Length: 163
Length: 163
Ligand SMILES: O=C(Oc1c(Br)cc(Br)cc1CNC(=O)c1ccccc1[N+](=O)[O-])c1ccc(Br)cc1
Ligand SMILES: O=C(Oc1c(Br)cc(Br)cc1CNC(=O)c1ccccc1[N+](=O)[O-])c1ccc(Br)cc1
Image 1 (cartoon, chains in turn brown, purple):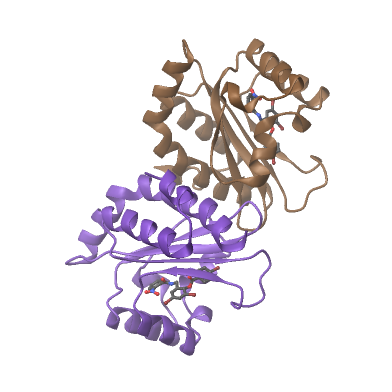
Image 2 (cartoon, chains in turn green, yellow):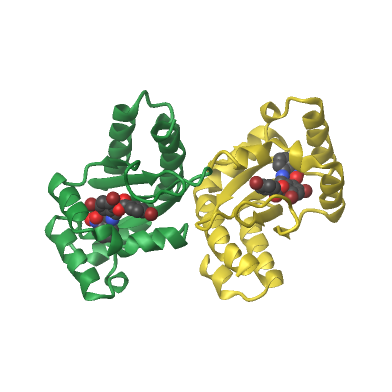
């Protein structure tokens, strides 16, 4: 089932299959980001998903890559970071949280990606939920499936992005 | 469950916890092996588990690291490789399979590990079964839990090994 991603014929079908897998699990918004080994910026970044255009533009223009707490987490860990109040420590980090929320992205998680050739990225997914308790229950129900998905997405996406 | 790995202090206790987690999922023999970023040999490796000593020594003395098809796989992929007839092709590769079988390690899988700081290794697990079909059913039944475990073991184990 997960293998349909590597079996996908091209970037278009991969991105579509990834978004549909996420959708079927219950996540209506996803962003897969991957950088080649030892990148100094995002010039060669492979970024694919269905996050709103306005938010993508705003995140870039505001330089939120340097504020977003899930980014530094990804450089230090292979474990998921859940979007919880505790992760936003500084005012800048709270402002990022509010801007994301205003854009419709409030509940979710970020799965770090570390590929066999030094690729560095994240798979982020947001769930449209009523409240945090509801978000938590949903995410726990699907977490083991998502844990497998992120590595399949990484292996397949790396081959598609940089070869 | 998974928190006990972090909670533990000492290589002996950590290894015993991992071994017990693996056993509970149906695997009686495991090996956790981890190398620092860009290692050029095995001198600085952290290798821990309950593989029999005679097999550990033979593998080393025979140079099976350069033959073992799971080793080259780990350098190329984040996805598991099942211990399968098809991964063996050369004469030395058939010899490796035969000797692993003689040591009682016939069915299993190797989960590649790629750490956030360039750590490289594998969690390899063997399952006792009447035949390969049965072994495959045992492994598939716990694959999502194993997928989480290998990442928890990597994050925790890298700290224990190198920090
Ligand atoms: O994908 C990455 O950052 C992205 C980019 Br680029 C654009 C946007 Br918009 C969002 C992210 C990742 N962050 C999130 O998805 C996120 C995390 C927590 C809360 C809210 C959000 N969010 O953007 O809605 C990224 C960058 C560097 C590294 Br290393 C890993 C991942
Ligand atoms: O752990 C690694 O190799 C080991 C070492 Br060292 C000693 C021994 Br004994 C075994 C391995 C890994 N291979 C296996 O466990 C294996 C794989 C397939 C079939 C049978 C076995 N086996 O050893 O029984 C390893 C080395 C390099 C990299 Br990269 C990743 C993993």
